[PDB]
Amino acid sequence: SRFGEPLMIELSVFLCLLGCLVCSLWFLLLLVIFSGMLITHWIVHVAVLYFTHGLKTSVEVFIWITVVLATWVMLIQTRKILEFVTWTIVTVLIGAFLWLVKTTLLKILASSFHLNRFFDRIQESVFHHSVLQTLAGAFAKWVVKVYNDQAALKHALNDNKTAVKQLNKLVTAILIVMMIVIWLIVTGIATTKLIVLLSSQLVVAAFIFGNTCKTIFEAIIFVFVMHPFDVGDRCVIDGNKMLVEEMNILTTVFLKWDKEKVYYPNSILCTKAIGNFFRSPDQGDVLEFSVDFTTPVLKIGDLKDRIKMYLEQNLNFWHPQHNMVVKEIENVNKIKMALFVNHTINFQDFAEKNRRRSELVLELKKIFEELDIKYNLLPQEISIRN
Amino acid sequence: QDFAEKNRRRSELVLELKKIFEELDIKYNLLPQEISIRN
Amino acid sequence: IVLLSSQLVVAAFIFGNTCKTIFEAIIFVFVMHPFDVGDRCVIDGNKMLVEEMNILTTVFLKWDKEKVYYPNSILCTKAIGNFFRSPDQGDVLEFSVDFTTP
Amino acid sequence: EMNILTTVFLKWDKEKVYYPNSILCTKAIGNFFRSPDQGDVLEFSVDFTTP
Amino acid sequence: EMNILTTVFLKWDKEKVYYPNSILCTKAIGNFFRSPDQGDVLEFSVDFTTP
Amino acid sequence: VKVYNDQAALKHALNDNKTAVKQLNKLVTAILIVMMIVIWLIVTGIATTKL
Ligand SMILES: CCCCCCCCCCCCCCCC(=O)O
Ligand SMILES: CCCCCCCCCCCCCCCC(=O)O
Ligand SMILES: CCCCCCCCCCCCCCCC(=O)O
Ligand SMILES: CCCCCCCCCCCCCCCC(=O)O
């Protein structure tokens, strides 16, 4: 596991000049320009940071084609051949448009997923590594924590890139297919019988792949929009405290307290209430106990006072705020009580939580012995027959 | 809305009930058990 | 125009159910409006403080401050208690005494 | 209170509860207000040997 | 064995069990083979007066 | 003889994890054949439009 483990190449400038040289008069000059008009788009782009760098090339294609179609329209059985060509160009532009849309949406999703959530953890990681580099020119525990946190960020970053690439493949594939169909029908190539068969194929597919498409969509919303947890977070699902090992579109992989690896479908996880200790504020806890009904109220008062002193001597572990609650009188034999305390940590480090609680439980033991707090069973009257 | 406060007030009432039972000598006892001994 | 409309129909067929869910969540948040941020609510016996409200999810803190994310698509079908909006509340102390108590 | 989408109830300890009509309408609902005089039961036990 | 419609498993007592994949598709599945070294717990109790 | 018996055991151990693929192949092929029948009927013009 990742967590829990024990020459032509640069001839474009020249090519562009050669293309310009192609005409100096007349009507076909725009058509000729199209052959190397990409250079013009590149220059326009130069003339025109995450989105900018990632999208400029998609924009260039879109506008490039738009111009080619516009000049084509204004340029002019060759009669039917040209109708065909015109529509082919239109289809190509539609394709580029959709391409641009697709790219944009994935860039938004991919970026906002992390940029608006853990920017600050990245900066903390950089800081600590700068410090380690400087130092080189409980210390060891600190050093290990710094490396483990960096690894966690690397894993989150890689899983996001992967998930987005998977989305990219699904969308690209459907986009390509629909563009083929669009081309065939707008150009007039497909005939009535072909339209009928394509129509049927789509309808049938709509049923077959219906649940699949819905499931993927819901999984995307769960993972990227709701985002109840990240990689490495300790989460609670139906009472199971589990560490998130990996996130994917269809599944989330978790490690149980005993490090069993669990594959948990997102289509199920989407309907559950999910806890997240990593994202929690300092967490609290409870120690329940019972005392005899005859315990003097003064000993109850001494118990409260002794507990307060303990907690105040250990402020690295406990917040000063606590409550002692008397809850119930059972028969006239038992008083049920509970101690409510506040930890100075959240529970991402579960073992540390238990160690601190364990000491508090032993302190309670000690206080009861010193104050002579006891619990007795009710007496039983016996009658003897011979 | 404030649970800690609710419980503090309730705890005092529970301890008052304790006090009243002691002052009025109110008790609970288990049913007697008859034993036959065959040695 | 026809081709565009045709695909909207197909998309509806396939994703209409997720859109339905989002819409239902909108009605829960803005029309039913069972709670606000900072209120203590009771869901399935769990007394939780509302920390954040969103369209798709509600974030709550449990008594031990564990942060919990509930889909609104689930809260829409539950009965929700709200202590903030409640009038003065009552309580019970149960006990038992000997039969022979005068 | 009553509304179209949800009914609001108070429990015996007066917490206020929002209860969707979409779930409430599939439950059997008792109504004490509309009820006739109601009955009750005291259960108890005695020794077998009681004459 | 694995097939498209069903998965065949052996229980600890080697009973052969046939699961529809359509139901496994909705379950959380543990996999020991793929797991890192696993941990364990021994629970016990002692007298309160143990020093 | 041990070498050949071990070779056989290994070939089976490896082939046992590919049974789902073989099943998918049969399914895909059946679909593909049907698609080609339909294509033949249409591309040669033998089918008419009412049918
Ligand atoms: C259902 C159509 C495919 C869905 C999109 C591609 C896969 C999305 C990611 C899900 C996890 C699959 C890849 C990891 C498998 C593994 O554990 O080796
Ligand atoms: C009719 C549905 C179409 C829109 C599909 C996109 C998903 C709905 C809008 C998401 C709004 C943000 C939800 C809260 C996210 C958060 O928990 O921070
Ligand atoms: C999908 C549309 C839902 C809106 C139509 C129903 C109108 C609201 C019904 C009452 C429930 C909300 C209470 C609002 C307060 C009020 O106006 O009395
Ligand atoms: C060709 C369509 C048949 C309908 C059933 C769909 C699955 C294709 C057939 C592959 C076999 C599925 C597993 C059954 C167990 C076995 O083969 O022994």
Image: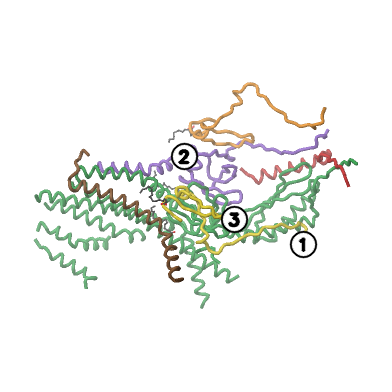
Chain colours: A green, B red, C purple, D orange, E yellow, F brown
The structure residue drawn at horizontal position 18% and vertical position 49%, both measured from the top left corner, is A87
Tell me how far mark 1 sits from mark 2, CA to CA: 60 Å
Q: Which mark is residue C30?
A: 2
The yes-or-no answer for disc 3 within 8 Å of ligand 2 is: no
Q: CA distance from mark 1 to mark 3?
A: 33 Å
Q: Are marks 1 and 3 in contact (CB under 8 Å)?
A: no
Q: Which mark is residue C13?
A: none
Q: Chain of mark 2?
A: C
Amino acid identity at mark 2: Phe
Judged from the image, the quadrant occupied by ligand 1 is bottom left
Q: Chain of mark 1?
A: E
Q: Nearer the viewer, residue A41 or F20?
A: F20
Do marks 1 and 2 share a chain?
no
Residue at 54% x, 59% y is A260
Residue C52 visible here: no
Q: Is residue C77 left or right of residue E43?
A: left
**Amino acid under label 3?**
Asp
Mark 1 — residue? E51
Q: Residues within 10 Å of mark 1 (few under 14, many from 20)?
A: few
Q: Secondary structure at mark 3?
A: loop
How far across and how far down the image is residue A26, in percent?
Answer: 9, 58
User: Which residue in the rendered view is the most extreme toward the front?
Assistant: F1
Report if residue A234 is visible in the image. yes
| Vertical relation: A171 (above or below) D41 | below
Q: Quarter of the image holding residue A378? A: top right
Please state the horizontal and vertical placement of residue F24, each as a whole percent of the image. Answer: 37, 53
Label 3 sits on residue = A282
